[PDB]
Amino acid sequence: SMNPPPPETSNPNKPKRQTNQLQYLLRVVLKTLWKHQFAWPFQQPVDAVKLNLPDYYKIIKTPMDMGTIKKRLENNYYWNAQECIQDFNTMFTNCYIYNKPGDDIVLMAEALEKLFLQKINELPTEE
Ligand SMILES: Cc1nnc2n1-c1ccc(Cl)cc1C(c1ccccc1)=NC2
Image: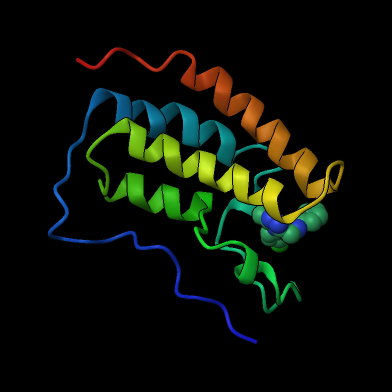
C-alpha cells in the first residue's frame, strides 16, 4: 500500500502575504482547533497505510489536514484568508465524504467545525 505525496506547504514562486485576517487564522482559528481533545486525527495527513484504509485516496482526491494548514500559515504560504478557509472546509468535507454519519471521526470533525465556524464568524475586517 502507498500514500500520496502530501499537499504542498512550500512554493517559493507563489506570491505571499501576511494579512491581519491570516494572522487571526493562525493565532485564533488554528490554535483553537489544534489544542482541542479531538484534534489528533486531523494534525497530519491521513496515513492510509497505517490506518488500513486502502480506498481513502481513491475517494479523497483533495486531501487536507491541520498539519498542512499549520505549515502553510507558519510559512506564509497564502495570499488571502479565503485560501486558508477553503483548506479547513476541504478537511471537514473530506471527513464527511469518506466516513458515515455518527462515526466517531465525524463527531470529532463536527465538534472542530462548530468551533471553526464560531471563530471565522468574527474574522476581522481586512486592515
Ligand atoms: C481525519 C480522518 N478522516 N477519516 C479518518 N481519519 C483519521 C485520521 C487519522 C487517524 Cl489516526 C484516525 C482517523 C480515523 C478515526 C476513527 C475513529 C476515531 C478517531 C479517528 N478515521 C479515518
